[PDB]
Image (spheres, coloured by chain):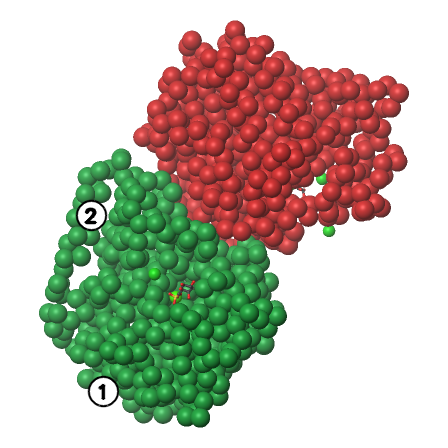
Chain colours: A red, B green
């Protein structure tokens, strides 16, 4: 009653403008739009980072990812969340929640002492950082191993055909993108052209594990079934479900029933699938009469990207679609579209519909949920997570004044509508070339007023150097922070 | 010194983001960017209307186009500016200016009593509403007759092969788009598939006049040559040159030297050509040492359109390019991109470089030039044109607080960053279907705050119903205005 269920939909690479309730016209997202229409949609909400693993780290620890220098993790990275580190699911466990995760992990698995043996129990993982149940795509959809990991075991593995991966050289006898292009459903760049699983090459080589191979085009069935089973089993008790999409990350291989539903190719059709999958979970909540007393949160790990490694026509068939809305940048960028993402709260018993323009941070989910449940936080716990339950539940309330934005190549700072980008000597020309996204680095400081210049086009750094200095000093204060408030 | 030259570059359908100095990365416009770098670039400047003829009418009469119900004129429409109406070129003539126009007219030509006889002298026209010299594309590039009109005469017309046009039925023996698709340089929709001139079908049928046919791919030479001659001849005297591009209107048929300069097809290559043509006129002013004492204004008649009637791949090869920047809509729309256009002032002897965010109106060019030259205006003259010479010349000065925006299906109103759109029952679904642009009509009133919602996505009408009433009242006051101030 006083402990509502929490379901956190976490989409992969969903851009600010990829929902029809955020202005999309080339794709319809009716299931997600109903949540927004009956809840609050936020226009200035942010992931911690512009790439997956750092934003997932900050969601779960309530702490900026640079404090542990988290970057995009490889398929065999060790777990980046410590087994005694405070986490949002662990926090929820102490008040009686059953916690589950279904879908993408990308937070590392194992201790790192020795390579993960995919044929033994895989630990530590989700179950050691506060999850009671986990059903994972271990790394990313485009990184081997292309298998599911349930709790501690690879699903449907045969002792007769053990599983190994290698990210430096070919092992095993699977066809590859570079040797066998005639077997490919989509062309792939050099990073992505290794072992072929289910007609698509991945990053890295995979040996064995044939019976454990997943089937991309039925991710929507597999994950939604597991999510439905978890909810149904936990229905008599408070539960936390983190539903971690592979959509709309590459390779986009949507179920055949969504193919051609848009004129944007595989990327647009993945948005349709992603919306269907959400409806499956929402309707299960409704039919068990859990929906009005569930805090549903729908959001994204980073901003959007069209061309991310496969020849899936995402850029050729973009049409009129503005995947990042009016905002400059995208995935990997320090401009606004790197972290400014869709963010929807739906909680009928407590949250009246509205639209909030408050500067809001996913990093504050930890402390705001702790506030909702009366959980005190230690002075060293989730140090960046602020109690923002009030603007989270009420569209008229303000939230942050200041928020740091993070990428590997540069840090930035929002202060109200001011946007500051720290200069860097680092060279990231591969983002413009390969990703068709301006990463946003300049060897000069950048300052923008988003009210008049929402697309970050007119650098005001030389017009307001005192403002630049003030924002850089504020960014240093945050980098140096070590306890709460 | 006190009577500077005025050269007004007026581009066809140039979107807010189609210049590299407004953020374009898929096309470079170095000549125009140099004008912005050494002058004022405006970020909130507006044509009066979202279509050609109403915005040209308002440019020349200093009066909103709805006061005469001006709409897109077909090729044989009569002159919409009366021979005794006060006009900006007529105003300039009384102060010692030689006035010329080179390029697109689209303001009508007959007196309306009888159809224009293209084989006789064509009057009234530019010479009857304040121009001393005119070399015209009479209607639009895609409307017959595909001939030039110099002063009162069709250029290179032969009595032995007289010229006739018909917009309702086929006349003459010219091939047509519907009969002879194998002759077309580009595919055409039904409105555009009539008489073939120079390998491209047009709107309407054209008979005779073979020697007077223009050549689209040499418009850049013809118009820049005519503008260079006019400047060269009038160089010893103050002059006003209105240089009215066909670029980047359909059909986009740029000179061969610009083909392939962008990866956007014919539309992108037309932006490059348009930039070359501007440089030709700018460099002629420089060679005659007139550039420093010339007020150069570069702007556009309405917002951008990709698919406007020909299969020129404008939408298929758009790539990452945002022709309207962050703004919703485009050509034909009542949303911001309908009228929010590029606007650059270059006048080194009086105008210091800068970027201005002031709400600015092309309609105010009449009164602001009158102020610059000390010309008093009658109480019934250019009634919507306000003196805004100060923010025109100074990037630090504010201009308008209120501005009405015009389309045939609905009117709108800006008040600071508030945007109000009046409701309408009228049906313009063909804009979405044929033009891939949201025309912006809703049966309900719309109100947006552009500071937080620059893309006009969150209707605030029901949250601030008093603000709606205020702006509707301001809009009616303007509709009822009849004199100046
Ligand atoms: O959303 S993320 O998981 O952070 O994306 C990780 C990315 O790694 C990059 O190195 C690849 O080229 C991308 O294709 C993508 O896999
Ligand atoms: O810039 S404008 O002259 O207003 O464009 C006029 C437009 O009229 C429409 O009926 C045609 O489909 C367009 O192709 C275009 O010619
Ligand atoms: Ca991601
Ligand atoms: Ca136009
Ligand atoms: Cl990285
Ligand atoms: Cl990698
Ligand atoms: Cl490559
Ligand atoms: Cl019209
Ligand atoms: Cl010359």
Residue at x 25%, y 56% (from the top left corner) = B404
Secondary structure, mark 1, is loop
> Of discs 2 and 1, which sits in the foreground?
2
The residue to which callout 2 is attached is: B472
Q: Which mark is residue A277?
A: none
Q: Chain of mark 1?
A: B
Secondary structure, mark 2, is helix
The residue to which callout 1 is attached is: B96
Q: Is residue B389 above or below residue A420?
A: below
**Which residue is the extreme one toward the top?**
A236
Q: Is residue B268 above or below residue B103?
A: above
Give how far across and how far down residue B332 sits, in percent.
37, 57
Q: Is residue B239 above or below residue A313?
A: below
**Label 2 with label 1: CB-CB less than 8 Å:** no
A21 or B386, which lies in front? A21
Residue at x 19%, y 43% (from the top left corner) = B469
Few, some or many C-alpha atoms within 10 Å of disc 1 (few <14, some 14-19, many ≥20)?
few
Image-quarter location of ligand 4: bottom left
């Amino acid at each position: 009653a006083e402990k509502p269920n929490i379901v956190l939909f976490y989409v992969d690479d969903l851009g600010w403008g990829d929902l029809s309730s955020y202005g999309a016209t080339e794709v319809n997202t009716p299931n997600i739009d109903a949540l927004a229409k009956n809840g609050i949609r936020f226009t200035d909400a942010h992931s911690s980072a512009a790439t997956s693993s750092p934003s997932r780290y900050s969601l779960l620890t309530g702490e900026h990812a640079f404090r542990k220098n988290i970057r995009i993790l490889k398929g065999d990275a060790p777990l980046v969340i410590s087994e005694v580190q405070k986490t949002l699911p662990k926090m929820l466990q102490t008040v009686g929640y059953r916690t589950g995760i279904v879908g993408k992990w990308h937070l590392g698995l194992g201790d790192g002492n020795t390579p993960v043996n995919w044929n033994e129990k895989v630990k530590p993982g989700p179950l050691e950082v506060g999850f009671d149940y986990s059903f994972l795509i271990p790394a990313t959809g485009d990184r081997v191993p292309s298998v599911f990991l349930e709790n501690h075991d690879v699903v449907n593995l045969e002792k007769s055909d053990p599983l190994f991966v290698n990210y430096q050289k070919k092992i095993g006898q699977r066809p590859t993108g570079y040797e066998n292009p005639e077997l490919l459903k989509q062309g792939a760049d050099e990073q992505h052209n290794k072992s072929i699983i289910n007609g698509v090459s991945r990053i890295g080589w995979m040996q064995g594990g044939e019976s454990a191979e997943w089937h991309d085009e039925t991710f929507n069935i597999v994950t939604s079934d597991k999510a439905k089973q978890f909810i149904s089993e936990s229905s008599k008790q408070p539960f936390f479900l983190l539903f971690s999409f592979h959509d709309i990350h590459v390779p986009r291989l949507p179920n055949e029933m969504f193919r051609g539903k848009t004129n944007m190719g595989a990327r647009g059709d993945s948005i349709v699938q992603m919306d269907w999958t959400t409806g499956q979970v929402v309707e299960k909540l409704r039919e068990l009469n859990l929906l009005d007393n569930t805090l549903v949160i729908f959001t994204s790990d980073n901003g959007a990207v069209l061309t991310d490694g496969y020849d899936d026509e995402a850029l050729k068939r973009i049409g009129t679609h503005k995947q990042n809305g009016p905002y400059r940048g995208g995935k990997y960028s320090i401009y606004e579209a790197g972290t400014r993402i869709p963010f929807i709260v739906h909680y009928p018993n407590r949250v009246k519909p509205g639209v909030s323009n408050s500067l809001f941070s996913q990093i504050d989910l930890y402390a705001s949920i702790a506030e909702l449940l009366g959980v005190p936080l230690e002075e060293t716990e989730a140090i960046d997570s602020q109690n923002q339950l009030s603007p989270l539940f009420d569209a008229s309330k303000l939230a942050r004044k200041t928020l740091v934005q993070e990428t590997p190549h540069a840090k930035g700072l929002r202060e109200n509508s001011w946007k500051y980008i720290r200069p860097t000597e680092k060279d990231v020309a591969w983002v413009k070339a390969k990703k068709n996204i301006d990463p946003g680095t300049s060897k000069a400081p950048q300052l923008f007023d988003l009210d008049t210049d929402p697309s970050e086009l007119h650098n005001l750094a030389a017009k307001y150097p005192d403002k630049v200095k003030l924002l850089e000093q504020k960014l240093q204060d945050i980098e140096l922070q070590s306890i709460r408030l």
